[PDB]
Image (cartoon, coloured by chain):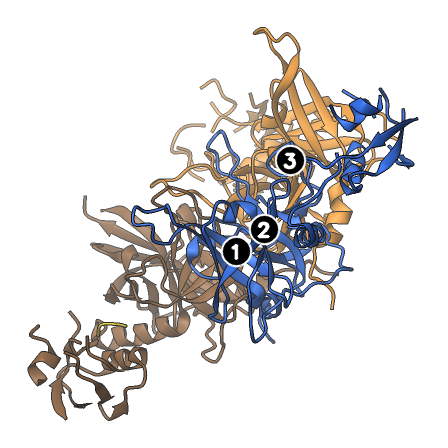
Chain colours: A yellow, B brown, C blue, D orange
C-alpha cells in the first residue's frame, strides 16, 4: 500500500 | 605466510574518497563530511545533509589537492548530493562494478573522515539489504552494515574486499527514545541507486519524479483532473500487477508527459512530485 | 577474483533464526495483545523445538515466532531455566521447518570468526561479524558460575535468543546479553556473551524431557549434607575444582546415595 | 572446509599478554593497599621486561603482573615516559617466560587485520578483531611530535598497555586509549589508538638503559627563555648538526645533552  | 589484510581494497578505493567541508558565513566550517569521486569529469557524490545551506563547499583529496566545488544538485528523498570540481590533472575515481550483486555477509570497508581525524577505514560486513532505514515513513532502500560509522563518515564510500563501491555511507543508528546506544548499526545508500540519482542530478540539476496523485484506488492531482475505488489494470500501456513496481514506473515518467490509464481509458498528464 | 564474504554461513544458518515476540493481555487497558518485549530464537530440529532466552519470554501471555520465509506461529513454552537464562519453545509446524546447522564435534576456539544472527531493535534479521573473544566466562553476574562465550560481534536489544555461528554456519552459541554493565555510564564496546551450544543443547534436552532443569542439591564455608553429618576430598568416588564438582552434584539424580569422603552417606535431593 | 579463524595469532601472542594492577595505599582509613586502576602489558623478551602504559602504573605503591598460565609477580618499575605514555616493568623469578612475536621488518599497512589483546573491565583476557584504520595519527591529544596507529578493534578500560597484533601474531602496537567524547552527543564507535611497535621498542630500550627517556632540547624552517638557542625569532634554520632542515625535532631529541652542534649551540636535556 503506497502513495504515488 | 603473510598478514591477512584488506589493504588492496584500500589502495584501490581510498584515494577516491575526499573530505567535504560545508562552510557558512559568520567563513567557518559549519559541518563536514565525506564524498566519493565517481568519474574523471570531477563528479562527486555525497550526502545532502552534509552540504545543506553551505555558502562554500570545499573538497580535499588524499593526495593533497583542494578545490572549491560546485553544487550540481541534491535530493532530500535519498539524501544524496552531487558536486563538481575541475581538474586538469587526472583524478582518482572509485572502482565500480555495475554487475556486482552485494550479498549479506560480504566484507565491507567504510571510508570517511570521522571527527576530522583524517581519512579512516573501518571493517564490517553487509548486515542486511533493502532496509527502510531509521524512518518507517521513509520508503527507501538501504544497505545495513556493522562497519563502524561516525560523524564525518556521511557521504563516503562503502567498498567490498576488491575495492568496488557497495554504497554511500549516510548515517549511523545513534538514537532511541529510551536513549539506549546502538552498536554496529549503520546505513548506506546502495551504489546502484546512488548512480541512478547522480545521473539524474547531473542532467536536470534535481531529481524529476512523476506524480499521479493516487490495483485498488483507496486533490487537484493529475488523477483527479483526468477523471476512488477504481481499479487500475494498466498504466502507460504497462500491466499494473504490483503497486510497488507501478509507483516506480510513475516516478520515472517525465512531467508534462501524457499516458493512458486504463481502469474498469483516461488521459492523465504527469506532474512533478511536490 | 570474488569478494571476501561470510554469505555462505548466512545462507546455511540465517533461515533457522526466528523473530520472537512476547505479547501481553494486561499491557494495554483494552486487553488486546501487544508486544511487551522481543528478541530472537533458533529452530533446533524439525519437531518445532526452538531455543530462546528466558528473559525474552518471561510472563508472556502469547509468544509469537516469525520465520524468515514469512510464516508466523504461536509458540508453546516448554520450559525455561533461570540459571542459564535459556528457554525452549515449540511451534506446531506443517510442511517442514528450517533447522540450525549443528556440528557436535566442533570445538570453538578463541579467535574463530563468528556471525551474530538476530533482530536488533526489530529492524528485521541482522547479521553482525566478530570473533570468539573468550570462553568459560561467568558473564555479567559472579553467581551461578555458568559458561559463556564472549564475542565482539555487535549485539543489541532484540538479538537475545538468537544464533552465534562460525564461518561454516555452524552453531557456536545462543546470544544472551550485551555487556551494558557500566555503573560509570562509560559505554562498553564489543563485549557480548552467548551460551556455548553444547550447554544449550544439554539444557534443551533436559527441558524437553522434564519441563525444567532438575539439579541435584574443598573447604566447607535441613539439607542433605546436614542430615549426613570440613574438607571434602572426594564426592561420589570422584576427586574434588569446586566448579566441576557442583556440576557433578547437579547431574546426580535425587534419591541417589553417594559417598562423601571428608566417609558419610549423603542422599541427594532436588534443588528448589 | 575449516572455520575461518585468527586462533593462530591467539596461540602465538596471547600467552605473553599480561594483566597489570596498579595498587596504592589508602591513607583514608582502609589502611591496606587497593586497586587504583588496572590494565594490560606485553612481555617483550626472556629477561622479563614488559611494556605497558604510563597512566596505568602512575602513582603505584605496588605493581602486580599476572600471566595467563597462572603465575603472578611483583613488578619493578624500570621507567616511564609521559610524552609517549609508555612504561617498562620487570619481573624476576623467571622459569621461562612467554614472549610476544616480533617482526621488526614487518611494515603495518592500512586495512591489515589486527587483534587487540587485553583485560577489559577485568573480565579476563579478551581478544577483539579489527583492522588498521590509519597511521601517523596524533590521537585524542595535543601533538607530542609522535604518531599512532588507529584501529576499530574494540578497546575498553583495561585494554591499555596490551598488545595489538596482526593475523600472524606479530606485535603491531601497544593499545593506549579509546576515543572519548562527542561534539553532538553521539557515542564514538571503533576509534582506538595504539603506539606503533617500532616506537615502543625504541622507547623501551631507552628506558631500560637510562631509566628514563633522555631527549635533546634546543628551545625553539621558520623560527616562530634561557634556552640553548637563546638564535632570534623569524630566523630561518636551513641546517642543524650538518643535516638539511618533524624530522628535525626527532633529530634533536636523539642528540646527547652537552653535545655542541652547528651558531654554536649546546644541547640540553628536556625537562
The answer, for residue C26, to whether it is visible in the render is yes
Please give the chain letter of the residue carrying mark 2.
C
The answer as to whether the residues below labels 1 and 2 share one chain is yes
Q: Secondary structure at mark 2?
A: strand
Q: CA distance from mark 3 to mark 2?
A: 18 Å
Q: Secondary structure at mark 1?
A: strand
| Of residues C256 and D177, the one drawn nearer to the viewer in this rendering | C256
Closer to viewer: mark 3 or mark 1: 1
Closer to viewer: mark 1 or mark 2: 1
Quadrant including the C terminus of chain D: top right
User: Which residue sits at x=76%, y=35%?
Assistant: C269
**Residue B38 percent coordinates (x, y):** 38, 71
Using the image, tell me which numbered label, if any, was put on residue C175: 2
Q: Earlier in the sequence, mark 1 or mark 2?
A: 1
Name the residue that disc number 3 marks. D123
Quarter of the rendering containing residue D55 = top right
Task: Tell me if residue D90 comes above or below residue C43 in the rendering.
Answer: above
Using the image, tell me which numbered label, if any, was put on residue C40: 1
Closer to viewer: mark 3 or mark 2: 2
Please give the chain letter of the residue carrying mark 1.
C
Using the image, tell me which numbered label, if any, was put on residue B132: none
Tell whether label 2 touches label 1 (CB within 8 Å). yes
C81 horizontally vs B134: left or right = right
The answer, for residue C235, to whether it is visible in the render is no
**Residue B135 percent coordinates (x, y):** 32, 58
Q: CA distance from mark 3 to mark 1?
A: 26 Å
**Residue B142 percent coordinates (x, y):** 39, 65
The answer as to whether the residues below labels 3 and 2 share one chain is no
Amino acid at each position: 500500500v503506497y502513495q504515488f | 605466510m603473510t598478514p591477512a589484510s584488506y589493504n588492496l581494497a584500500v589502495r584501490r578505493a581510498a584515494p577516491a574518497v575526499v573530505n567535504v567541508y560545508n562552510r557558512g558565513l559568520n567563513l567557518e566550517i559549519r559541518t563536514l563530511g565525506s564524498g566519493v569521486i565517481m568519474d574523471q569529469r570531477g563528479y562527486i557524490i555525497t550526502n545532502k545533509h552534509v552540504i545543506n545551506d553551505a555558502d562554500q563547499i570545499i573538497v580535499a583529496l588524499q593526495d593533497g589537492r583542494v578545490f572549491e566545488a560546485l553544487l550540481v544538485g541534491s535530493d532530500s528523498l535519498t539524501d544524496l548530493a552531487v558536486l563538481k570540481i575541475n581538474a586538469t590533472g587526472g583524478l582518482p575515481t572509485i572502482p565500480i562494478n555495475a554487475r556486482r550483486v552485494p550479498h549479506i555477509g560480504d566484507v565491507v570497508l567504510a571510508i570517511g573522515n570521522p571527527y576530522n581525524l583524517g581519512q579512516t577505514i573501518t571493517q564490517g560486513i553487509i548486515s542486511a539489504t533493502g532496509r527502510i532505514g531509521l524512518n518507517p515513513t521513509g520508503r527507501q532502500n538501504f544497505l545495513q552494515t556493522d562497519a563502524s560509522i561516525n560523524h564525518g563518515n556521511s557521504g563516503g564510500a562503502l567498498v567490498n574486499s576488491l575495492g568496488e563501491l557497495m554504497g554511500i555511507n549516510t548515517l549511523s543508528f545513534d538514537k532511541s527514545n529510551d536513549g539506549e546506544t546502538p552498536e554496529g548499526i549503520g546505513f548506506a545508500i546502495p551504489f546502484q541507486l546512488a548512480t541512478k540519482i547522480m545521473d539524474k542530478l547531473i542532467r536536470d540539476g534535481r531529481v524529476i519524479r512523476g506524480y499521479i496523485g493516487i490495483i485498488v484506488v483507496n486533490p487537484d492531482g493529475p488523477a483527479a483532473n483526468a477523471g476512488v475505488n477504481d481499479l487500475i489494470i494498466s498504466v502507460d500501456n504497462k500491466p499494473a500487477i504490483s503497486a510497488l513496481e507501478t509507483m516506480d514506473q510513475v516516478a520515472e515518467i517525465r512531467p508534462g508527459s501524457v499516458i493512458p490509464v486504463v481502469v474498469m481509458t483516461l488521459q492523465v498528464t504527469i506532474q512533478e512530485y511536490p
